[PDB]
Image (cartoon, rainbow, N blue to C red; front, top):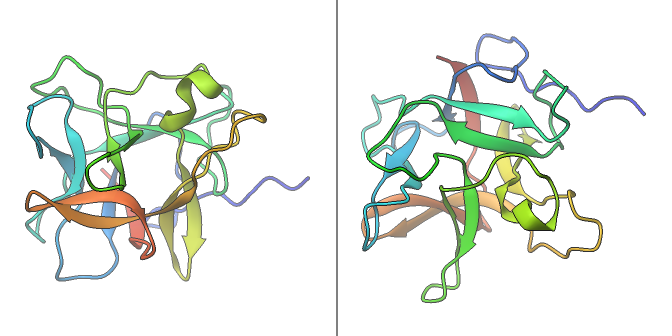
Length: 179
């Protein structure tokens, strides 16, 4: 088969693994780039949120394809996503989807384990898909052929006053700025 298209940054260059990017909103006037915050009861692990302030790019992160050797970040392909800088938490900055019993939402949190694609890490794999002239983030892993993950587009869901990321009927349109 043809390889799926590379994801392009805001300067038109192919995204690569091991390179810092900001995930920025395409629709203006709602918030800034993606970042980490303590949203709930405990401080750690941190949750993935949109910055309150529109001027902020948020925090830089990287994408690592499921096929370790591969260097280009492509659409329709599972990735581990993690923020680059250290935080107040020992737990990793690697994105993980988690079901919240009290809201019925599936939120993006952190503390994910890297690699080992399969049922054991099912919730740690994310896709980028085309969305008009930009992109959206999607959870629908194909790392486990006998698993039946609950798939969805990632959108914004307000919880405890934070702009959390969760599976949503309204995709959050994003673009990728090389940091």
